[PDB]
Amino acid sequence: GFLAGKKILITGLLSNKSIAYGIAKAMHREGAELAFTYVGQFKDRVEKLCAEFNPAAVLPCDVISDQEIKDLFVELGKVWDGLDAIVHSIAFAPRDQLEGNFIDCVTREGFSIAHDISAYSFAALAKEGRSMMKNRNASMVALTYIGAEKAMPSYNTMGVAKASLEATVRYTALALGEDGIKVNAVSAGPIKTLAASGISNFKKMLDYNAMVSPLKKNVDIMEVGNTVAFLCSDMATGITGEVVHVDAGYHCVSMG
Amino acid sequence: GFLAGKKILITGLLSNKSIAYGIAKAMHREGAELAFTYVGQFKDRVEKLCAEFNPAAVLPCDVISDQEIKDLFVELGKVWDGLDAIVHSIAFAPRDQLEGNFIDCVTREGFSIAHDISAYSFAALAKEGRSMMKNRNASMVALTYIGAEKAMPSYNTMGVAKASLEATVRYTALALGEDGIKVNAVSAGPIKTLAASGISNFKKMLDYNAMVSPLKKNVDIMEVGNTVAFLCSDMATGITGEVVHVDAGYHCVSMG
Amino acid sequence: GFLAGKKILITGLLSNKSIAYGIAKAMHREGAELAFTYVGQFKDRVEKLCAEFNPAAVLPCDVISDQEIKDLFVELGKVWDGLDAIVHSIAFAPRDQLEGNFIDCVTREGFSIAHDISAYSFAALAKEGRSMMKNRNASMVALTYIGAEKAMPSYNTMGVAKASLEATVRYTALALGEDGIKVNAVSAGPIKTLAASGISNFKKMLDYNAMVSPLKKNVDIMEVGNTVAFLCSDMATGITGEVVHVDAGYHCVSMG
Amino acid sequence: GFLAGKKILITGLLSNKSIAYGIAKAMHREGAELAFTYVGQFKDRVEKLCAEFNPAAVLPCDVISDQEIKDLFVELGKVWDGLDAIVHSIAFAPRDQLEGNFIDCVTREGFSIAHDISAYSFAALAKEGRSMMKNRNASMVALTYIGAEKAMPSYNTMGVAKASLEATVRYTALALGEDGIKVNAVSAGPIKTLAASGISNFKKMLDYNAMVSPLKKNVDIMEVGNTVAFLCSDMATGITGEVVHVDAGYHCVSMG
Ligand SMILES: NC(=O)c1ccc[n+]([C@@H]2O[C@H](COP(=O)([O-])OP(=O)(O)OC[C@H]3O[C@@H](n4cnc5c(N)ncnc54)[C@H](O)[C@@H]3O)[C@@H](O)[C@H]2O)c1
Ligand SMILES: NC(=O)c1ccc[n+]([C@@H]2O[C@H](COP(=O)([O-])OP(=O)(O)OC[C@H]3O[C@@H](n4cnc5c(N)ncnc54)[C@H](O)[C@@H]3O)[C@@H](O)[C@H]2O)c1
Ligand SMILES: NC(=O)c1ccc[n+]([C@@H]2O[C@H](COP(=O)([O-])OP(=O)(O)OC[C@H]3O[C@@H](n4cnc5c(N)ncnc54)[C@H](O)[C@@H]3O)[C@@H](O)[C@H]2O)c1
Ligand SMILES: NC(=O)c1ccc[n+]([C@@H]2O[C@H](COP(=O)([O-])OP(=O)(O)OC[C@H]3O[C@@H](n4cnc5c(N)ncnc54)[C@H](O)[C@@H]3O)[C@@H](O)[C@H]2O)c1
Ligand SMILES: Oc1cc(Cl)ccc1Oc1ccc(Cl)cc1Cl
Ligand SMILES: Oc1cc(Cl)ccc1Oc1ccc(Cl)cc1Cl
Ligand SMILES: Oc1cc(Cl)ccc1Oc1ccc(Cl)cc1Cl
Ligand SMILES: Oc1cc(Cl)ccc1Oc1ccc(Cl)cc1Cl
């Protein structure tokens, strides 16, 4: 496997529909040694779910908290000497930020929170994980959406938070490059996950991608997972600060 | 004047050198009726600066506060029947967010504050000004910088907040379009302003720009101001969600 | 007028529906001294049409021919000492390049011809006009379409030619910057012109822009013309290598 | 191997240092069955180079000729029941198009030739290969360069042709998508190849890249080859119309 022996932390695994689940399946297939995080109460749920990946550790991490993130790496460091990659597959904005007219709905705190969790958390993981990642062709990958690049209905302040995220990925790539850490993002097309039901427009978005996309289909978590996997491999060491669209080609067309 | 009669609110006027000053000069030349905001204790400084423009109002507004933004437009509603444009020329991030390695310097709070004042404040002005701007070919312009698009040394968290601001400009353009309101940004090249002091490598950027850009020069506040004035005129009613680079062409080249 | 006394050459004027016609109206309004080109047989047609703009010259120029382009500037130079701007508002691809599946329809020669006329002609005009434009804040503007940036049905090899054009604009901006010549493009939304009937998809494209665009409308030749006018003014001397979308905001959104 | 069984045609193999050589090494390692084309008198040189790959066929194809491209696929149809991928790793422009000021150097013919071989030839391969690639998760990859996106010294007409090639990649992706064929490009950083000799400022670009890019290094043909191999694999079936930068992050930064 092209990830054989690599030590990789996966965030955001919630159900077997999660993009993180596809990433896990892909990386496990390729020989990676995998660890996982969960938020507070989903402990036993995620614990059962990720067992099938022979995890080196399953640890709590609500990225809201500087403490939990710091402790995540303290505990992870009791299990692993160093770390090969961090996979960031997590976002959040209050529900009222994801419906209706953007200007009607947006609020100062919702904006703040969407950004705190969906964008800042990526650089926070980088900050704490850096020491374990130093000097080993380490990698980071974040999940984003085309809502960052173009305005669209519903996605609203999450769209704005994704743009912050993509920029954070670029600045993170610049900052950590000297340590041989590559930092990239996968821009995934619409996939029916738990988080997706939180988007007003989702059924429409999903249907629309299939019709308009060049490949005339929706993507799945294995296409996404496989791409994230590659981006944590030695084959991808020339790639950094990049956004790769895994969206059946939706990003390259206009009209349809 | 191609702004004759138009009622425009200008934020960010701090000194003789502010970009907002160039904007003000340009719009006053073009027949605009102007209002200005100030923060903190700069009431006298700003009144003195903007006196030559015969402003209708010089009002307090620290965009950290929702109430002040709300009261700004209530007071404005007392001198003006309606608003033609809002010029957003305001940004802030704590000094420790603008020096050294991005991952070293980044903090949750500094991230939050940068986004809150540099980006959220644009949508906040849009939210409270919206009713006065409805249905008169109204306009909004924000000031951004190429650090939103590309990572660069030192700009760090502001770079990320600027990416957030540009996405906010797009979603705002989408949200306000049905009201005939166009929403755009001007991406200015480095100009020597008071804020530029907070950029550790600023003299670097300025000299680099002049040497590398096609027009082999630095831009000035009138170049930026004229462009902002244009983007508030009836000539630009076909343009929204756009970012216009006023940077002597720096944006279009690679190497020099 | 903000173009008062400026000497500007306009190409592509064919009917009073032409984008070039809007550009002419706008620049004449702003005090510009205007000259025009035509292709071979449209001589008397264009001659009648542009009379209303008090043209300094109306000259033949089929950009297919290196000879006619060279002679255009020889004759123009008998009338004007120097030249302030060139407006390129011309494109062509064989009809069979603009219908159906791109791969089915595209041909080596059609590709060549689309590029020769729609892209190369811009740099050819720059090459010959340069000497008259030297050292006077001169300008060039080309018309493009979003078909360059994104693949779309029908537009096909014209889309590919527009991408070449936009790149030619950037390389031209780099090359001529040292002479103080600024070089930009306006990316216009769909407008019902003569050339438009040559596009299979046009009615659909037109209708689709109105529904999806933030400003919920189609643009007109005066919005486009006014923007081109501004881009040939002293107000725009900080702008070069830029593409400005005048498309009611279509470019910034996804879905609708 | 993640290309096991896949039948892939590789163009552009000229030497030990060609990018096509890195691509070939990577795909042979991953289980691909390979074929190669050559131009002119390099039949013996290429057969000798690609012998270790146990190619199914080493065939003549100068992409200036439609007939040769047509006959290529007829001959290929004699060894293979179907084609899984085409690697386009080929460009050309006359030397006088790659030195000095772009406007000084550009000619109609040099423009035409650059586009014809560097860009049109990609769609031409797509046209004639299409029937063998139908409905097998087939793939196309072209090699491009950041000179398509930004203007830079010397690259000149090739820069423009590369912009044309990237648009062709998008329209081809749109056209071939219904056939399950994904179409992408790899944007490689400067690598020391035979062609690089024709770039007057190449040692400039190479040293600049290593100093300025986040990973503080130059890319190599295996980094590019691995990525191209990935883009021909079943793992990448969610990706089309994409451009992936394999440039040590150069694309994402500004200043250094
Ligand atoms: N589903 C899609 O169509 C799609 C498309 C593009 C991008 N993405 C992105 O992919 C990622 C995965 O989302 P998903 O769609 O698989 O949904 P999901 O519901 O499976 O995953 C959402 C994850 O975010 C985690 N999360 C939320 N707040 C957190 C916090 N404070 N700390 C730690 N974890 C937190 C949740 O536990 C959950 O595991 C997200 O970044 C999402 O924005 C999803
Ligand atoms: N100077 C440059 O090179 C340059 C380049 C690109 C973009 N910009 C942007 O242009 C804008 C104007 O900046 P400038 O360079 O003219 O500097 P400046 O220092 O003259 O103006 C900055 C303004 O931001 C205002 N501000 C800061 N915090 C505020 C708050 N909380 N509430 C209300 N106002 C607040 C300040 O009062 C000040 O007037 C900024 O958005 C800046 O990021 C500047
Ligand atoms: N109509 C639209 O929706 C639209 C949208 C975006 C961009 N554009 C671009 O704007 C420009 C103006 O086109 P238009 O739509 O106003 O159509 P139009 O039919 O009025 O103009 C087409 C012009 O190109 C000229 N032309 C063609 N071949 C020529 C040659 N070999 N030499 C000299 N002139 C030649 C024709 O004479 C004509 O004047 C074109 O570049 C077009 O691609 C048009
Ligand atoms: N070397 C770099 O730094 C770099 C960077 C970015 C992109 N690229 C691109 O990668 C590709 C491979 O180039 P390379 O750098 O490995 O150089 P190379 O000289 O090894 O390969 C160039 C190939 O183009 C082929 N070619 C030229 N004209 C042809 C024609 N008419 N018909 C068929 N084949 C023809 C040549 O035979 C040769 O094998 C090119 O598209 C190039 O533009 C190279
Ligand atoms: O970013 C997404 C994009 C799409 Cl199309 C579907 C789901 C996405 O992911 C989320 C959306 C909203 C919230 Cl609150 C949390 C997450 Cl993880
Ligand atoms: O965005 C800017 C970009 C440049 Cl090149 C120069 C000044 C800028 O403006 C700021 C920079 C830092 C802070 Cl704290 C506040 C402001 Cl207004
Ligand atoms: O580029 C265009 C885009 C649109 Cl939506 C409409 C018209 C356009 O202009 C042309 C289209 C085809 C040919 Cl043959 C010539 C020209 Cl001038
Ligand atoms: O595109 C390239 C970019 C770089 Cl940095 C180096 C080599 C490249 O490839 C070429 C450059 C010029 C010619 Cl004539 C032919 C080819 Cl294949």
Image (cartoon, coloured by chain):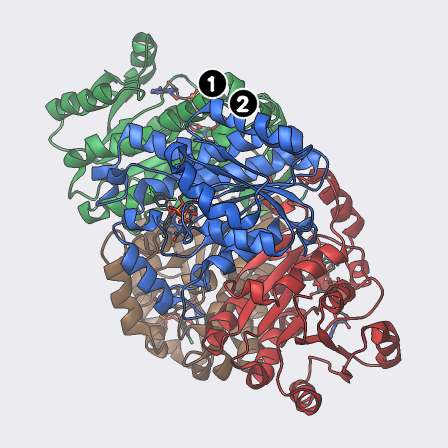
Chain colours: A brown, B red, C blue, D green
**Is D83 displayed left or right of D223 in the figure?**
left
- Tell me: is circle 1 under 8 Å from ligand 8: yes
Figure quadrant of the N terminus of chain D: top left
Residue A45 image position (x, y, % from top left): 34, 76
Q: Tell me the crowding category of disc 1: few under 14, some 14 to 19, or many 20 or more residues within 10 angstroms, Cα based.
A: some
- Whole-angstrom CA distance, mark 2 to mark 1, is 7 Å
Figure quadrant of the C terminus of chain D: top right
- Disc 1: which residue: D94
Callout 2, which amino acid? Leu
Residue A210 image position (x, y, % from top left): 24, 61
Whether residues under marks 2 and 1 lie with C-beta atoms below 8 angstroms apart, the answer is yes
**Is D228 displayed left or right of C126 in the figure?**
left
| Residue at point 65%, 86% (across, down) | B66
Callout 1, which amino acid? Pro
Residue A92 visible in image: no
Quarter occupied by residue A41? bottom left
